Image: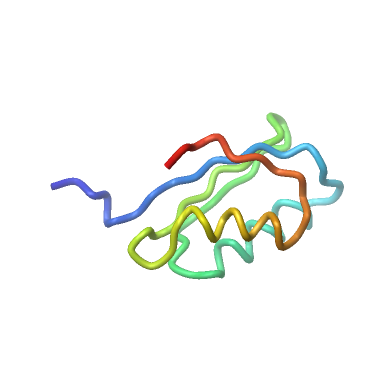
Length: 79
């Protein structure tokens, strides 16, 4: 099989930040919320890629994550 260590990846766009603390502080919590392996942001393209263990969490937490801070960020992955 090839479940890739039972994990999934979710990418989202961004258009409302200011200082590194913006996405980086957000990526820190979303990465410190559970079994989040790694993540990364790129103001160059206004977006950020992060993963998350579906066996422990899911794409819903990510939805609640943005709704928790406010950074107007939109996802681009259906599942």
